[PDB]
Image (cartoon, rainbow over the protein chains, first blue to last red):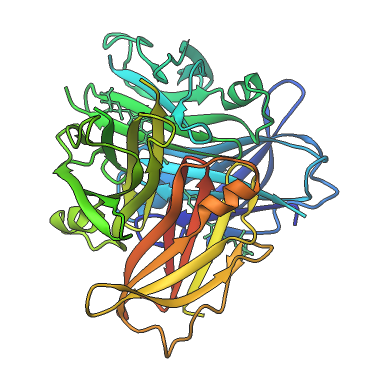
Length: 115
Length: 116
Length: 116
Length: 115
Ligand SMILES: O=C(O)[C@H]1O[C@@H](Oc2cc(O)c3c(=O)c(-c4ccc(O)cc4)coc3c2)[C@H](O)[C@@H](O)[C@@H]1O
Ligand SMILES: O=C(O)[C@H]1O[C@@H](Oc2cc(O)c3c(=O)c(-c4ccc(O)cc4)coc3c2)[C@H](O)[C@@H](O)[C@@H]1O
């Protein structure tokens, strides 16, 4: 699994479950092409997005549909979505974990890049 | 000043100075139209991006050019930029502060929204 | 103003108003001696805690009473308080801003340290 | 495992390995009594701190020795340590994960409380 997404809810102190996540790759003409998507599990994780073969060097965008998540909880949030944009680079370690911590008017994201 | 951006550096414990910021607005055709840009000051603040008149209802994207910041400091960071996308002024005019706290492999952004 | 505290609320997108803050200094006997206290303003800021003369070198603990804040708002949060423990002024006087961003089950704190 | 600690490094984008963690319980006389301790693993996690039998309701303090961590990397940090103080409560879910994200002048902590 070269790319994993983990989402946490800072209001409830829980995984953020059933959050839609869309991954895009930047194409030559500077547009964003769909690449992978899924919904977080009961543990707030989304595995199996891509394969080592498919996940080549490039710029990627991970879009997390935070607005739907909060609205389903009856909370009006600030952001349309959370967006994580990064270059995948073969130099560094093999596995990318993109973590996000959600509040209604804030989010934090960190990358854990390991072998 | 209805839109302000403040950026801190979690490695140095300082304002993040000279951080480029580009703001876009979603147009009728659903493309991102350039709206305003600037750079943070010595206090890590960026004022004067827009006016109450021009900051109409819409979906805005605040791009904070974190890679250019870390690279200008000779550090290789993870993200290309921090993106903050939100609907503004859809219940009337508000004042928005977008705050961001930067590390090379992490950032945190929050909004402070007040009613004038 | 050598020690200031600023607190934001990540649920409301607002300053965190009326947050109690207690500051302690580690004494010669290694106990925490009360040093200064106050409450954040309508801007989420707390000024006037101490003076340059009284803010000598030492290990300080800034306790931000987050539970009392969330409970005063009728919310049941996770933490008792946010604690920020640091050595101050050991290379000469500095100005410290302790910022904190609060959610019911999470907080983030950063320091901005400047040289007057 | 009713109490797990996970520590991440926001400068390197990695688990924070070999970080000392001390857990204390608040005793009747308002002092902090040692309760459990350990060092984070290669995955930045510290398991096996306590047992369900031992982890009763009460106020606990998790002290993470961030200062030593940064100094071992040649970085001068701000905090003496990171401190997480909370009440354990039998009402809510069973398992506490205390997560911390470390930078030299900042840290963030969130609780993930699950069944
Ligand atoms: O000029 C003003 O009137 C006020 O501006 C504030 O600037 C900031 C600036 C900030 O930049 C932050 C932050 O950045 C965060 C923060 C902390 C952790 C995170 O994970 C995310 C955000 C909290 O409070 C803040 C305050 C000053 O602290 C305050 O003294 C001053 O009077
Ligand atoms: O089971 C899995 O497959 C994987 O679950 C993930 O667990 C977590 C769990 C977490 O709990 C966090 C966090 O909580 C923080 C965090 C803290 C404060 C912030 O402001 C932002 C992020 C970031 O990464 C994380 C990762 C890990 O990637 C991995 O150890 C585990 O095998």
